[PDB]
Image (spheres, grey):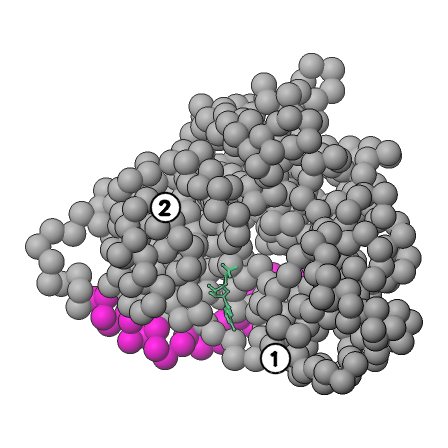
Amino acid sequence: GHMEDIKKISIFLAYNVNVDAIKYLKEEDIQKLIEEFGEEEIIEKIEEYPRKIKEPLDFVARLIHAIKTGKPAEVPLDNEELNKWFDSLFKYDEERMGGQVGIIANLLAILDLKKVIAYSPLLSKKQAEMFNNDLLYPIVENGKLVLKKPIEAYKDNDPIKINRIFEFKEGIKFKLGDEKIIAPQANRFIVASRPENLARIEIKEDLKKYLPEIGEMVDCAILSGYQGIKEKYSDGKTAEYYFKRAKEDIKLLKKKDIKVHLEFASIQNIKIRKKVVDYILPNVDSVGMDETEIANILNILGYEELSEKILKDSKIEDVIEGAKILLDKFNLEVVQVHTIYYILFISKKDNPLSKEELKKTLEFATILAATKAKLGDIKNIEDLKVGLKVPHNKYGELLKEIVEKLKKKKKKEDYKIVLIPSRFVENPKSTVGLGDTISTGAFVSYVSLLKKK
Ligand SMILES: Nc1ncnc2c1ncn2[C@@H]1O[C@H](COP(=O)(O)O)[C@@H](O)[C@H]1O
């Protein structure tokens, strides 16, 4: 319980919240779709490969197409006027809080943090009910900034962003025409739209003036959702407009002294990914990422040779070298890299924390990650004891010894490098958003130990 000095942490979170409505597909389900829509019409439609869903058949064909590959896919609805028709035709099994803000803010509430301020542009009644009741939502009433609970700041008439997810296990089998189909791998087919018509990824004009005020009452922030920003919008606005104003929010928050953290998401649009590199990464204090994304960042900065060595081979010496480049280039205090086997932490030599403390930050991150992996969602702090029963990966212990040897050889260590093995869960319940869980655990723990000093 001593580690839980974190409960003394207050934190601000923006920008992405949504509702996840999940269907857990079984063979019978796909069978009913085949019967109700027909085999030839689906087969013909799969050849068509619609890029957006306009008629119910589009969804049937793209869902089956994806199931054939075992690879992930996202197709938006053609128009938000089809939402309620879609939800009555293809009903969900369960509804849930989605989005990096909504998921992590709810977890930080369950971890009893001092103050957790979460912000999203849309706050419909159904959405606001998904929040943990301890969360605070910023509001400007009567020329003053007021933190109120979400079930008391919601607005009727507000739309609701919903991600429709269809989960299919490995090996789900069904016939289509003569083609017998087997799921090569477990994957999820997602029906969802990036915001344009209904909302945008930004702090509204009214709240902007109060960002520095939010900066005073908060020890740290975690910002996310930049993968939802579009290159061009119909109203003539562009990614640059929103990325510029996203840069402004970080700068307004940092008039006062806070740490800002970013978890580097897997943005498949390279032009929007390059925007995150240019507008967000240089202005932030902490970053977390996997092996794939550091190579993707190194490739944007021009280290093409290094990027492929990490991608092809994954040697820890190369990941450490790539993390050192990120640390020195961008005004960062720390860089975090996570893989199924290890978590790596690097900070300049003048970091107020000791190598001993940095390892404690990491230890707590592996426990929290292992709790969620074995239990699915975390619902209580008691659950962290389940993660403590998960032992360290044996190959990571080997990498720890390797890093220790590396450090002894070099003449000057102007850096603090700490690696611990992960608490791998072999037959995990869930794997989604595990990266945000680990990265948040280490960052919050890191902010704690800084605050004690
Ligand atoms: N079975 C598992 N047990 C513990 N952690 C896992 C497991 N599978 C995946 N992870 C973590 O999930 C992360 C994936 O993060 P990302 O794909 O960036 O969201 C990896 O870096 C691992 O640390």
Residue 92 point in image, percent of width and height = 82, 62
For the point 51% across and 41% down, the residue is 272
Amino acid type assigned to the residue bearing label 1 in the image:
Pro
Q: Which residues are magenta?
A: 378-404
Q: Taking 158 as reference, is 63 above or below it?
A: below
For residue 49, say whether it is visible. yes
Q: Residue at x 36, y 56 (%)?
A: 295
- From what the image shows, is residue 208 above or below residue 2? above
Secondary element at image label 1: loop
Q: Main secondary structure of the magenta part?
A: helix
Compared to residue 313, the image places residue 141 above or below, namely above
The residue that label 1 is drawn on is 184
Q: How packed is label 2: few (under 14 Cα within 10 Å), some, or many (20 or more)? A: some
Q: For mark 2, what is the residue?
A: 300
Q: Residue furthest top?
A: 143
Q: Is residue 187 left or right of residue 280?
A: right
Residue 273: percent from the left, percent from the top? 48, 44
Q: Is residue 222 magenta?
A: no
Measured along the vertical axis of the image, is residue 319 above or below residue 145? below
Q: Amino acid at mark 2?
A: Ile
Which disc number belongs to residue 239?
none
